[PDB]
Structures are given as structure tokens and as C-alpha cells.
Amino acid sequence: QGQNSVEIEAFGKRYFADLYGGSIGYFLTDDVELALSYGEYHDVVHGNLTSLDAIYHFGTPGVGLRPYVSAGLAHQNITNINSDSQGRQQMTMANIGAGLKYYFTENFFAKASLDGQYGLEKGEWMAGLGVGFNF
């Protein structure tokens, strides 16, 4: 782990609709990771969300718990097919989040997350879980 390491992750989040996806992340330092994520909406409508986030990790690299906080920008593409209408919408939103990543081996982690997405014109919050591998 630490600076220059890479992480691949699978996630699944539910609003409190579901979002299921993956992420690739790179450690700019021992604590700061840049991650690109992609997810598709299911179970409440079709669409997807692409996100670029900066994640600050508390604790230290290695086996154990690294809480984190994150912020980023996302682009959402939604198609809605309804009984007498349909449409498509694309939107940019700001993200803030926090969570717990537990590295139970030097390479593998499980994560529990809370994320808020905010409209930028004129928020929506999810809880989630993910798993990943750091190399």
C-alpha cells in the first residue's frame, strides 16, 4: 500500500434505488488517493454515474482500519421511461463522503461508505459497501 499503489474496487450503494459499480484508484501519497468510478443504477429508470474523487485516508497504510473522507465531481446520465413520457437527462453533481476501509490483509479491503451527491443549479445520500485489492 502507500504512495504509488493502485486499488481496484467493486461497490454497491443504496439511497436512503441501487448503484452497482467499480473503481480504479491511485495513491498520490500514503494518504491521498485519486479514484475514477463508474456505476449503473438498478431497482428504481436506467442510467449511470461516473465520478472522480479525491480520498483522504486516516490511519496508516498496512493491515487495519483506515477511515476516510472524500470529495469529487460526478456526471449522471439517466433515462426515464414512464407510462406517457420518456426522456434523458445528463447532470453534473458534487460529491462528499466518508467511510471505513478495513485492510484485512496487506492487499485486500472491505469498505462501508456514506456518500452525498449535490445538485449544482438554482442532496441525495447513499450508504454502501465495497471490496477491493491494492497492489
Image (cartoon, rainbow, N blue to C red):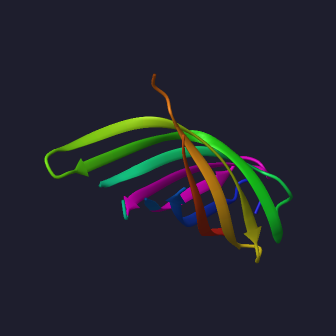
Residue located farthest toward the front when viewing the structure as drawn: 83
* Count of marks placed on residues: 0
Query: Percent x, y for residue 12?
Result: 52, 65
- Seen from the viewer's position, the closer of residues 18 and 102 is 18
Q: What residue is at 63 percent from the left and 62 percent from the top?
A: 7
Please, what is the dominant secondary structure of the magenta stretch?
strand
**Residue 131 magenta-drawn?**
no
Residue located farthest toward the top when viewing the structure as drawn: 122
Q: What residue is at 25 percent from the left and 42 percent from the top?
A: 88
* Residue 27 visible, this orientation: yes
Query: Percent x, y for residue 15?
Result: 51, 56
- Seen from the viewer's position, the closer of residues 130 and 27 is 130
Say whether residue 2 is left or right of residue 80.
right
> Is 109 located above or below residue 21 in the figure?
below
Q: What residue is at 34 percent from the left and 45 percent from the top?
A: 77
Place residue 65 in its image quadrant.
bottom right
Say whether residue 44 is left or right of residue 23.
left
**Residue 34 magenta-drawn?**
yes
Place residue 112 in its image quadrant.
bottom right
Q: What residue is at 32 percent from the left and 47 percent from the top?
A: 78
Residue located farthest toward the left when viewing the structure as drawn: 84
Query: Percent x, y for residue 73?
Result: 53, 38
Assign the N terminus to one quadrant of the image.
bottom right
Say whether residue 30 is left or right of residue 87.
right
* Residue 62 visible, this orientation: no
- Seen from the viewer's position, the closer of residues 44 and 89 is 44
> Is 26 located above or below residue 120 in the figure?
below
Residue located farthest toward the bottom when viewing the structure as drawn: 105
Assign the C terminus to one quadrant of the image.
bottom right
Segment colored magenta: 20-42
Query: Percent x, y for residue 53?
Result: 60, 45
